Amino acid sequence: SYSGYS
């Protein structure tokens, strides 16, 4: 998964 800011 991705968490945060992209």
Image (tube, grey):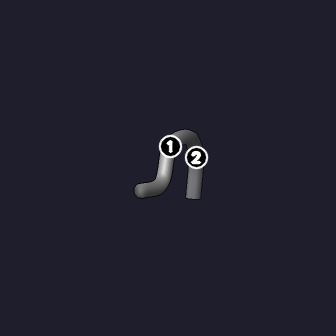
In the rendered structure, which amino acid carries the disc numbered 2? Tyr
Q: Residue furthest right?
A: 5
Image depth: mark 1 or mark 2 in front: 1
- Residue at the extreme front of the image, as rendered: 1
Q: Which residue is drawn at 41% across and 56% down?
A: 1
User: Residue 3, how many percent across, how many down?
Assistant: 50, 43
Task: Specify few, some or many for label 1: CA neighbours under 10 Å numbering under 14, 14-19, or 20 or more.
Answer: few
Q: Nearer the viewer, residue 1 or 4?
A: 1
Q: What is the secondary structure assignment of the residue under circle 1? A: loop
Q: Distance between the residues labelled 1 and 2?
A: 7 Å
In the drawing, does residue 6 fall left or right of residue 1? right
Spot the residue most to the left.
Answer: 1
Q: Residues within 10 Å of mark 2 (few under 14, many from 20)?
A: few
Q: Residue furthest top?
A: 4
Residue at 56% across / 40% down in the picture? 4
Residue beneath disc 2: 5
Q: How many labels does the image show?
A: 2
* Residue 3 image label: 1
Task: State whether residue 2 is above or below residue 3.
Answer: below
Residue at position x 58%, y 46% in the image: 5
Quarter of the C terminus within the rendering: bottom right
Give the residue type at disc 1: Ser
Q: Mark 2 falls on what kind of element? A: loop
Q: Judge left or right: residue 2 versus residue 4.
A: left
